[PDB]
Amino acid sequence: FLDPKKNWLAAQHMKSLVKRLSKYGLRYDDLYDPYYDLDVKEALNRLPKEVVDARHARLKRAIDLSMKHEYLPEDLQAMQTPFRGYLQDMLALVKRERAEREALGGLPLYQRSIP
Amino acid sequence: FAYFVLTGGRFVYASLIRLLVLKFVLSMSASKDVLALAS
Amino acid sequence: ADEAEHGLACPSYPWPHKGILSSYDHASIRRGHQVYTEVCASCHSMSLISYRDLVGVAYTEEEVKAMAAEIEVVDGPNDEGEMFTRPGKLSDRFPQPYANEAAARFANGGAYPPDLSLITKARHNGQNYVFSLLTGYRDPPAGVSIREGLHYNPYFPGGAIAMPKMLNDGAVEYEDGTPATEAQMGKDVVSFLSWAAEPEMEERKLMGFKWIFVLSLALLQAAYYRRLRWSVLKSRKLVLDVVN
Amino acid sequence: ASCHSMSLISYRDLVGVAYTEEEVKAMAAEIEVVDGPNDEGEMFTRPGKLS
Amino acid sequence: PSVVKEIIIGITLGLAAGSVWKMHHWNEQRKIRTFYDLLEKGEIGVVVD
Amino acid sequence: GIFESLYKVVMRRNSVYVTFVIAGAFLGERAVDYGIHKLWEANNVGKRYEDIPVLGQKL
Amino acid sequence: KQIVPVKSVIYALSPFQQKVMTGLWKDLPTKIHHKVSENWISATLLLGPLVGTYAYVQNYLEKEKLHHRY
Amino acid sequence: MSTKYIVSAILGSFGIAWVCDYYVSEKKIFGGSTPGTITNKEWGEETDKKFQAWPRTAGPPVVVNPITRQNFVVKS
Amino acid sequence: PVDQKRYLEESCKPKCVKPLLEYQACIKRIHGDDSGQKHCTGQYFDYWFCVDKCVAPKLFTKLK
Amino acid sequence: IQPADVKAAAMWGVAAATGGLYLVQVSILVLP
Ligand code: HEC
């Protein structure tokens, strides 16, 4: 795996993602839907309230901008941290706990409801 | 101004609805060959 | 080969009934019905058009009554179970020249002269194709000698068609003194055939114009209504307590 | 059969009920029936069939 | 705002327009050349009868 | 303004508004139909059924 | 299907105090520029295979017909 | 601001120019004449059919504008 | 009763004489051959396509 | 309140009759 700092294509991809995410004022982790995985749900429950509330505020701002058909002003676009993640470590810990629980005879702590 | 724009569109819609309803009912009405055979 | 199989392509003639506001040339419809009756009804049939269809389109009602009274059709059983023939009325369809498809094919060398009611909608590029087919009885190219019993026609798929060159100069005498030539006769008969295939064209065009205009105005109203209802949402300022 | 008609009972209905197939075929071949236009376009007549 | 970019794109548009006009001129020249070529060595004459 | 005048006329009770709309639809449809008919007749002069020279000479 | 509150403060103006059909015309050049500069790549990937295949097909048909022309 | 006024005035100017043209050269509120070559309305017809074969004093009829009209005789 | 279509196509015959010349070239080749399938309907189609394209509007503006 | 109610009911009846005439234009009934 030669993604970062050694692949021109990967550098271009990172540039494009930074452009788009900062344009809407989002972060990469905010793209993780709790309804999608049910592990993101547990991670978001375990995260501190300040972090979760900031995530919700950023999501609401992004949806507002998407409705209005406009982007953040250049100032707030400059003051952006699209890849200052907050969810990957907790998500990995939750996945690891799930891994051991399934590894040695355990019921899942939560399951997706059949729709 | 808003209500008058809306009113113009509203009676356009009324015209459309009357057209459609009458088209269906008159289609279910009589036919030219029958009227010809009326003698 | 493939070129002759698909036939020489037909140009785009400027028909008088083409355009978002364009009507049939009704004098030309009358003239085309004359030429069809004179020369084309011997072999081809319509069988989907009543005499009453001509009333108010090309002939007056008394004229159509006389024309129908000219021909005689078989009417159902009388009080003895026998069959009889009575002059045609204003409701009878156009007469059929042959008893059935078998008789038609037998009279026309195995080839069946198609029903002409929907002929311009039953061919790709209908009206242009029919006009070109009628007018383009050309000398076959070099070294392509076609068999006896057919005629060369570049537009017909395969080049060999079964009907002979019918439209000739001076074939008919028009009522209104219009000089009868091959091109004029073709134009009139194709106008008549295109009317026969689509007798509702004028009403449909009028309805389409009126309703496209009216619905465009409705569209503007809809555009304004939506913008008005959404303007309390799109021009709103929210403070969220977050920066990055 | 000289006055009333059935016109809903085919000859094939009789096999296995009152007659055998050979008998029904012979009975059908007894009578004549008009048939659709031939290659010349005329309405001809042929001996009846089982159907 | 980039001055060199604006001048480059202007020169490029000028050359495109000139190329279109030159294609027109070349087609016209070919038509004239083939007409006279035939007029000497072909079926084409100029007097009607 | 004319908008405020017509509002004070026919936009204080919904029944009148409905009636006004009904009047508007009928009148506007008739006006558009007349205009389109005039346009059609202007565009297709000579081609009508009523003005063909042999309309009643077959008898 | 619960609703997550965000603790914002929202000011909104009534629809009858705003121009309703002017935002469509305010910035046409900027909006056209944004559309083109944001979607030229996607336009190339959409119309590219189509036009290329069409040109190839007409070219090959021309060659084939001229070759079979005796 | 004023684009309404400017465009309206431009269209009005075209209307006024049309009216003045119609009165001064179609009905000639100021006296004048019209050629016999344009009012006959069949002169252009023969002019075009003559571009097909233009008469000449010494020699058979000959064509004019052979290139720009693409009209010319064949093998003979 | 002179045919307007025939007269018009004769008039426009010298407009696009190039397909006609190609068709004549094939005619000469086929006359030289005199033994093959020898059709070359493609030249015929090209030439008559050009003539038909020419006689498109003039026919109806000349017709009654 | 009753006068206002009956006035409103009559107005709605007039609107309903106008809608009925619009849907079914009857000069045959209008003339007599
Ligand atoms: C008897 C002879 C006639 C007469 C007087 C006319 N037609 Fe034609 N026609 C006839 C036959 C036997 C056939 C079949 C040929 C075949 O399809 O192999 C046709 C065919 C047509 C067609 C169909 C062409 C096609 O489908 O590509 C048309 C459109 C047609 N005929 C028209 C037509 C018209 C308008 C006539 C009056 C001038 C006419 N035919 C006369 C036999 C005969």
Image (cartoon, coloured by chain):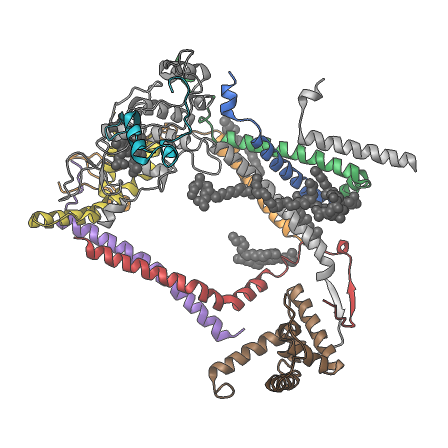
Chain colours: A brown, B blue, D cyan, E purple, F green, G red, H orange, I yellow
Q: Which residue is pictured at 33% across the width and 22% down the height?
A: C37
**Residue C115 visible to an observer of this rendering:** yes
User: Left or right: where does residue I24 sit relative to residue A10?
Assistant: left
User: Left or right: where does residue C184 sit relative to residue B11?
Assistant: left
User: Left or right: where does residue D14 sit relative to residue C168?
Assistant: right
Q: Identify which residue, C222 or C145, lies in the foreground.
A: C145
Q: Which residue is pictured at 63% across the width and 67% down the height?
A: A114
Question: Vertical placement of H35 versus C89: above or below?
Answer: below
The percent position of residue F5, horizontal first and vertical second, equals 79, 40
- Residue found farthest to the right: J1
The answer to which image quadrant residue C107 occupies is top left
Q: Quadrant of ligand 1?
A: top left
The quarter of the picture where the N terminus of chain H appears is bottom right
The percent position of residue C115, horizontal first and vertical second, equals 34, 31
Q: Which residue is pictured at 54% across the width and 77% down the height?
A: A16
Q: Identify which residue, A23 or J17, lies in the foreground.
A: J17
The answer to which image quadrant residue D24 occupies is top left
